[PDB]
Amino acid sequence: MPGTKRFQHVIETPEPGKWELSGYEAAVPITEKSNPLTQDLDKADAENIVRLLGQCDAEIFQEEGQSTYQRLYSESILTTMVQVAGKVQEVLKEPDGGLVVLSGGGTSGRMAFLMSVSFNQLMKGLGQKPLYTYLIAGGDRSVVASREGTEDSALHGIEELKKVAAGKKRVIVIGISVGLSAPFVAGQMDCCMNNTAVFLPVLVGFNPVSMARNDPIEDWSSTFRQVAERMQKMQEKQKAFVLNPAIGPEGLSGSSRMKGGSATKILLETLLLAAHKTVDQGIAASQRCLLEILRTFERAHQVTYSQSPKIATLMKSVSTSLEKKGHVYLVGWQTLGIIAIMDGVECIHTFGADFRDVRGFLIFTFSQEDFLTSILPSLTEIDTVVFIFTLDDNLTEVQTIVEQVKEKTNHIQALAHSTVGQTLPIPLKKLFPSIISITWPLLFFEYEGNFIQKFQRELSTKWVLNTVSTGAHVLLGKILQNHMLDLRISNSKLFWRALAMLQRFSGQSKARCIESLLRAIHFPQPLSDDIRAAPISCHVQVAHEKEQVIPIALLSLLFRCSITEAQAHLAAAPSVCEAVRSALA
Ligand SMILES: CC(C)(O)c1ccnc(-c2cccc3cc([C@H](NS(=O)(=O)C4CC4)c4c(Cl)cnc(N)c4F)sc23)c1
Ligand SMILES: O=P(O)(O)OC[C@@H](O)[C@@H](O)[C@H](O)[C@@H](O)CO
C-alpha cells in the first residue's frame, strides 16, 4: 500500500510493558534515548535541575563497563584519536596544498567554527599560514542563526566541500554529526572516500555505527549508516577514521547541542591540540598527551559545577523574567560572547522561543556605545542581563555597561573567569552581590595565546549557559518528562523524532501514529495516497510553517478523534501543556 516503503524502516510500537523485551529500547539511538536520570526533569526544582544536568554532563567522562559500548576513555577510542593526530601531523609538515576542514549542521557546525578559529589563531601566533577551515550547513550565516532545515541535503554538503577544497592536494575532512545522522555530512564523507588520493575523512559522533541513521536521503543513494560502515572498513588501512564514543543520553532527549556539542569540543580540541604540541617536539602524539588534556577538561566539569548553587539562582531569575513576558540578555566578550549568541539562538528551535526571549551580544555584534545607545534604552524592572567575561578582558568596557544597565534593571548577574590570584576591581565587584566566578588553577602551557585556557573557559561557559537556558524553560513547564514534545518539524530527523515521540506517549501502532501526524501536518487537506507516499521533505516543508502540530497529533490519538476536534479542545484548554498532561491521564 502507499507509505509502506516510506515508513518500512520505522520500528513498530511495542505492546505495553514489552518496550524492553521486543528489543525496542536496544534499538533507540543513544543520542535519542530518554536519560533515566532525567525521567522527572519536569518535576525538579531549579537546584535539582542543575544537579541532574551536571550529572548528565559527567557521563561524558564515565568509563566503559565490562557486552557494551566504547567510551571516551576506552582504549580503542584513544588509539583512534592518536592515529588521527598522526594524520593531522603529516598535513602540518606539508602546508602547501594541505587543508583541514571541520564540518557539520546546527550546533555541530557552530562547534566546528569556534575550533577552526582557535587553531588558525595558534598557527598564526606562531607565524605560519592557517590551514583550518569550517563548513556549516546553510553557509556561514548558519553559524549564528537558527536554520534547522539546511542539514538535509547531501549535495549541498558535497558542494561546499568541493568549494573550499579546490586546488588543494591533501585534505582532512572532519565531519561532525552527533547522531551520525546529518545528510550534509554523509555526502562529504562519501565524496572523500571516492577520492582518497586527496581526501582523508574522519567522522565524529556519539552513536555506535550500528545505530547510525539508516533513512533514505532524498538527493543521494547511500544512507548515513552505509557510509559510516564503509569508513569503518577503511580504517584498517588508515584511510578513514570513525571516532564515535558513547557519552550517554542527553538530559533533554535528543538535544544534542548539550553533551554532544561539549563532547565534540572536548574530543577534537584534545586531539588537535595534542597534534600541534607534539609536532614541535618531533615526537609521535601519544595516548598520554591526550590523557592530560582529557583529564583537564574533566576537572573543568568539576570546577564549573562547584558553582552549582549560583547556577541555579541565575536560572530562577532567567525563568521568572521569561514567565512575565520579559526578555533575557547574555552579554559577553570575544569568544564567550559568541557562545552566548549561539546559546540564545538555539532556544528558538529548541523551545519554541522568540529570538528576543534569550539573546546574546558580543562586545548580534553590537559593541560599547552602540549597545548603550541601541539596546540599553528599552529595558525593564523584570528583564535579566548576564555579563560573561574574564579578568583578562577590557574591564573598563565591562564596568561602563554594567553601570548604565544597573539603573534599567536590578536582575544582573555575572559569569567571571579568573586564574587564581587575579582579583576584581571593586567598582565591578560591588555591582554583583552573588557573582559566579570560576577561578582556574595555574597550569603549565606551551603556546602564547594559552589555548588550553580558552578551551576550558569556552566549555565551562557552554555548560553554564546550556544548563541555564534549558532548565529555565523546564521550570516554565514546557518539557514533558525529559522530552520536548512541542517541537517544530524543520528537518527529517525532527520528523522522525516527532513520530517516535507519538509512539512513545500514545502507545499506539505506527500506522496510527503516522496517520495522525500526517493529518495534523497537512490539515485541512485530507490524507490522499500522494501525501502518504510523499518524500519526508514534503511533510517537513508544510509542518515547518505550523504550530502545535505534534500535540494536535497526540490529542487526536489519545481521544480517538479528528484533527478538527483535537484543535477545538486544545483551544479550550488553559495551555498546550495543561491539555497534553490532562489527556495523558
Ligand atoms: C525515546 C523515543 C521517544 O522512544 C525515541 C525518540 C527518537 N527516536 C527513537 C527511535 C527508536 C527506534 C529507532 C529509531 C531510529 C531513528 C532514526 N533513524 S531513521 O531516520 O533512519 C528511521 C526513520 C526512523 C534516527 C534519528 Cl531520527 C536520529 N539519529 C539517528 N541515529 C537515528 F537512527 S530514531 C529511533 C525513539
Ligand atoms: O550533530 P547532528 O547529530 O548531526 O545534529 C545537528 C543538528 O541537528 C543539531 O546540532 C541541532 O541543530 C541541535 O539543535 C540539537 O540540539
Image: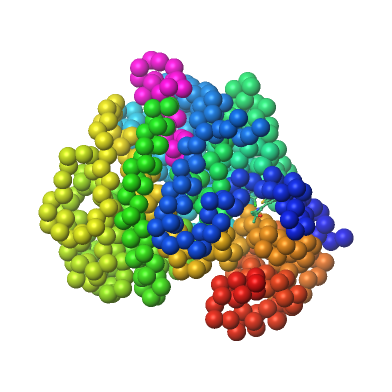
**Front residue of 473 and 392:** 473
Please indicate, yes or no, whether residue 99 appears anywhere in the rendered image. yes
Judge from the rendering whether residue 207 lies leftward or rightward of residue 381; answer left or right: right
For this orientation, the residue located farthest to the front is: 17
Question: Residue 42, position in %: x, y?
Answer: 51, 63
Residue 158: say if magenta. Answer: no
Q: Is residue 113 above or below residue 78?
A: below
For this orientation, the residue located farthest to the right is: 1
Q: Residue at x 47, y 61 (%)?
A: 44
Q: Residue at x 63, y 37 (%)?
A: 208
Residue 288: say if magenta. Answer: yes
Question: Residue 582, position in %: x, y?
Answer: 61, 75
Q: Is residue 473 above or below residue 461?
A: below
Q: Is residue 364 above or below residue 574?
A: above
Q: Quadrant of residue 511?
A: bottom right
Colour scheme: rainbow
For this orientation, the residue located farthest to the left is: 426
Q: Quadrant of the N terminus?
A: bottom right
Q: Residue at x 66, y 32 (%)?
A: 67
Please indicate, yes or no, whether residue 202 appears anywhere in the rendered image. no
Question: Residue 61, position in %: x, y?
Answer: 47, 37
- What predominant SS class does the magenta segment belong to? helix
Q: Quadrant of the C terminus?
A: bottom right
Q: Residue at x 64, y 57 (%)?
A: 497
The span shown in magenta is 263-289
Question: Residue 448, position in %: x, y?
Answer: 26, 31
Instruction: Say how many tags the image has.
Output: 0
**Front residue of 252 and 283:** 252
